[PDB]
Length: 48
Length: 48
Image (cartoon, rainbow over all chains, first blue to last red; front, side, top):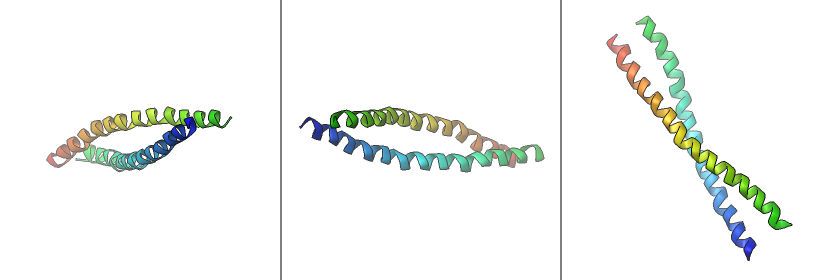
């Protein structure tokens, strides 16, 4: 009975790591769109 | 012997879930300091 409680902690772990996994992978994709913009508009700074 | 190896790959999950949650606050702060400049330089590059 010590196992099944401890096994359940994995069962609430493996969702939460998966729950953040979509939450992280969205936010880094929000970076690299806005990352390449601030390189792109930087060339529009010294041009303007 | 099953109780041992269930504990370890629970702990490395516990190692990552502290670290991963430490990133989502951090990369949000990395986002916001980038979120200024893409709102900042855009307000320059049209006024230029």
